[PDB]
Amino acid sequence: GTDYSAWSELTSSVNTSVSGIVDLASLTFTTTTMTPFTSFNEDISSFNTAVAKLQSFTSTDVTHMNQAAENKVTDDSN
Amino acid sequence: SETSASYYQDLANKESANYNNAISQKAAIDAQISRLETAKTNLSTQINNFQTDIVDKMSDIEGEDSSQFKGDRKTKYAEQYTSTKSAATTNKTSHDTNLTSITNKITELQTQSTSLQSAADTAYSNMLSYQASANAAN
Amino acid sequence: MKIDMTEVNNQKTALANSISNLNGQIDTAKNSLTNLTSSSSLTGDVKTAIDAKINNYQVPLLTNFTNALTTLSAQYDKTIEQFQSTVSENAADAVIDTDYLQGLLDNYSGIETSISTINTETSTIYSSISDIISLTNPDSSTITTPLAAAKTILTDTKTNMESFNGWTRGTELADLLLSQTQTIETLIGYASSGYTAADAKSFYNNNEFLQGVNKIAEAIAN
């Protein structure tokens, strides 16, 4: 059998935990102007860009998994 | 009369030579005094320039600002700065020592010039006495 | 162009704290995805495809993001190593400003000229009265030898500062994040079809991306 409530609750915890990943805080250099140390914010920004892209897919994949469960409920009921 | 006048005339001739020699030596000493006065004037000017343009300018390459220069590079740089500042102070002290030696040499030459003038006055008075005795002897 | 190792080490600690927080939140996201694979609330071939998708991509994607944080931390330490090796400056609070060093260098020409001119003048007055009293002119090279050596330090430091400022890191983190982006974009393209689609199922069961993330993590452990 398929328990849609338990499955939707687990996929909801997945979407919560993945979106619970915050941005990597950018470094603060007031007096330091060195390019090798200043350019680290570009790596931090590209990291948070890839993470935000995973979070957008996860929000879609959670809906995708929930639909597969209710399709399993509808087609197994027949 | 002929050996007595010739005796005093010979002594007057010697005192005349002593006067002319003392005056010439005094003129040479006075020439050395003038040259040292010139050296003392120009050395004092270069000593003042050594203080303002060298010793006083050292603080402009020190880098004592801890908010702009700190670490091992400052340590290696502060060491060479100390050797540079210590060498400039030593060289100025050397100039001050030579300036004192010049001043002491001027004082010693001025004392010698006065002695040469005193010797000339004695020789001229002796010459006048010998010349008077040689004239009266005939 | 200025650097303060005090600020750099403070950012190293702040970076380690943020990495610790992100690793904890990533582990929570890993456990939530693990609970799906161990759950019996869904069964059938669609559950087999979802389990293959999670174990071969979603969990490795979170693992590789932790590897990206470790790689970014290692690159920050290596950048500190590169600075302390190019400039030869191992101080933990070192402060170096290229403009301030140049300001100290802009006053050397006046001092060098004064030393050379006064040395020529004093040597002239000492030789002019040498027959009256012989006095020795002090050696000016006692000043100019450490003066030039001190100028070399300012010359070498400013040069290495400008030299290190052009140093570049490797593409390790850029190649890791590109692999993350390409994998996520592929999973996006398959989200419109079913989990049991022939092309999508074959992709979900391929464990090459998982083996690649496992190899990055194993290398990090040594």
Image (cartoon, coloured by chain):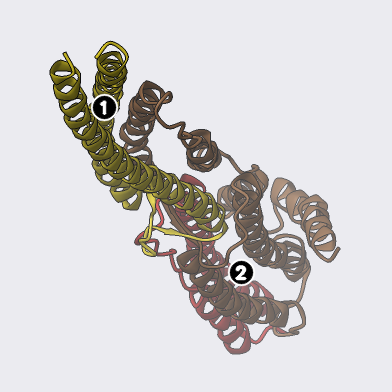
Image side of residue C137 versus residue C216, left or right: left
Q: Quadrant of residue B63?
A: bottom left
User: In the image shown, does B69 or B47 lie closer to the viewer?
Assistant: B47
User: In the image shown, does B59 or B134 lie closer to the viewer?
Assistant: B134
| Residue C156 visible to an observer of this rendering | no
Residue C94 place in picture, x, y as percent: 51, 61
Q: Which mark is residue B26?
A: 1
Kindly indicate whether the residues beneath marks 1 and 2 are on one polypeptide chain.
Answer: no
Residue C205 place in picture, x, y as percent: 80, 56
| Chain corresponding to red in the figure | A
Q: How many marks?
A: 2
Q: Secondary structure at mark 2?
A: helix
Q: Residues within 10 Å of mark 2 (few under 14, many from 20)?
A: some
User: In the image shown, does B27 or A63 lie closer to the viewer?
Assistant: B27
Are the residues tagged 1 and 2 within 8 Å (C-beta)? no
Residue where numbered disc 2 is placed: A68
Colour that chain B carries in the picture: yellow
Q: Which amino acid type is shown beneath numbered disc 2?
A: Ala
User: In the image shown, does B81 or C91 lie closer to the viewer?
Assistant: B81
